[PDB]
Amino acid sequence: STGSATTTPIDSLDDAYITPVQIGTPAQTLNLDFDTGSSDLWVFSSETTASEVDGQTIYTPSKSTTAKLLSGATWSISYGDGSSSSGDVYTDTVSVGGLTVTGQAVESAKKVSSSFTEDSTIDGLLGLAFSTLNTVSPTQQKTFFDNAKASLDSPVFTADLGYHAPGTYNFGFIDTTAYTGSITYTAVSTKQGFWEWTSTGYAVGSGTFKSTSIDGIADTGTTLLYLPATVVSAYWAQVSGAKSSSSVGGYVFPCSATLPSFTFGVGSARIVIPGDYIDFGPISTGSSSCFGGIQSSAGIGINIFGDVALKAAFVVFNGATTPTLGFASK
Ligand SMILES: NCc1ccc(C(F)(F)F)cc1
Ligand SMILES: NCc1ccc(C(F)(F)F)cc1
Image (cartoon, rainbow, N blue to C red; front, side):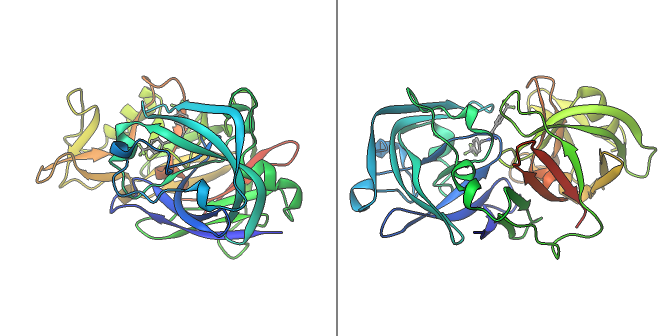
């Protein structure tokens, strides 16, 4: 079997992408944030503290004839940005673009952090990292991808994120019409539960390519590109007037500047991020200081190839017994 679903940016800056997901019988359609950096499928629900819901579409298990409460199971998650949520667990039927999984763990939020409440466009998250990171206790649960793997034509999914435009998540097949040239595959380490890989280096604009190993994770659930301080300093040094601002919390630049592209290596291949992808607009309404899309990972502890990098490529998440990541230009 296969599945295909359109994913849409939630705002004018591509801060996140939402994809419609059908849950329950009859279907309840929720717009979920597909997150290859986490492994919980959790949703706003009829059980969520009422004051913590502000416009989200909620999952109502009591209206689904296929929902079963997973007795005694709870979940609690904290994301690298400080957001968090927790609740109890149902199993139900979950469908993504024609691909159906029965008995999927659907984690019902009882409590969500403020950043989720204020995001009226995101009804929940669909985790696509490895199931070892799932937070359900006392019995760990599998991700949607792990549950679907056996019935998929090929144990893969692909991310084709758009720049200020819709894109596509495909499950079980590779669309050879969606990219140019060849796909370059690179080894993945699952030892931390992430889609973790090693980039072979970088270039700033038309500068010389620097061969150097950068270990990081492919994370559709993170907006920006977080790289080591040496690399990030080399990039912003090429933008007149750019500086790291402690009050803002990262590199800012004059909104009148033109940004250079950023190239990152995948084996012997190169993915080029156009400079416009790195502009995240004014730091406050009406400001002439703009926020940069490439930031330092020094405070994080791991390098993150977030949406800024991934949307410049066609990305294959190969969940074979030896997992790999594939990157192609598009
Ligand atoms: N998108 C999920 C996510 C968020 C943060 C991290 C961090 F910070 F731990 F790297 C990993 C994965
Ligand atoms: N990386 C996972 C993640 C995704 C979105 C959010 C937000 F935007 F809702 F806060 C937090 C954490």
